[PDB]
Amino acid sequence: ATCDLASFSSQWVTPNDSLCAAHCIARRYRGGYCNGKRVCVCR
């Protein structure tokens, strides 16, 4: 998807929605999984 498109290899912190997004969900967020820029900010 966004940022983590095709063969993922972002030169920053891995989106890892499986864990990062899951944590986001804990706080009423949809899921990070790398935002528009390249940070897994919860949203």
Image (cartoon, rainbow, N blue to C red):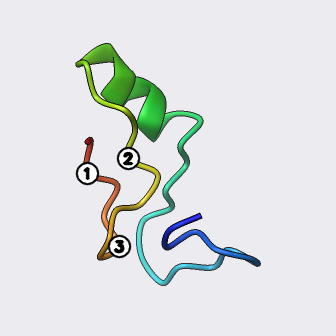
Residue lying farthest bottom? 11
Q: Secondary structure at mark 3?
A: loop
Badge 1: few (under 14), some or many (20 or more) residues near its Cα, within 10 Å?
some
- According to the picture, the residue beneath numbered tag 1 turns out to be 41
Amino acid bearing label 1: Val
- Numbered label tally: 3
Q: CA distance from mark 2 to mark 1?
A: 5 Å
Of label 3 and label 2, which has the lower sequence position? 2
Q: Are marks 2 and 1 in contact (CB under 8 Å)?
A: yes
Residue at the spot x=37%, y=22% of the render? 25
- According to the picture, the residue beneath numbered tag 2 turns out to be 32
Q: Is residue 39 left or right of residue 19?
A: left
Looking at the rendering, in which quadrant would you find the N terminus? bottom right
Nearer to me, 32 or 16? 32
Q: Secondary structure at mark 1?
A: loop
Residue at the spot x=64%, y=74% of the render? 5
Amino acid bearing label 2: Gly
Amino acid bearing label 3: Arg
Residue at the spot x=27%, y=42% of the render? 42
For residue 34, above or below residue 43: below
Nearer to me, 3 or 12? 3
